[PDB]
Length: 33
Image (cartoon, rainbow, N blue to C red; front, side, top):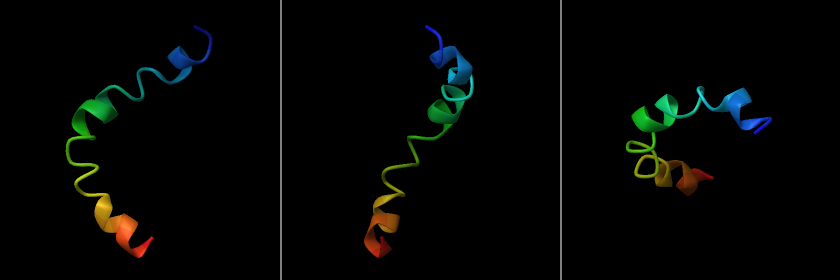
């Protein structure tokens, strides 16, 4: 509305591509963390 668009194109793709791999490849970091 007045901020999202300032970072709407950035995400999407990044998300589309990412996410899937993420989560299942994050719990590993949560370990050490």
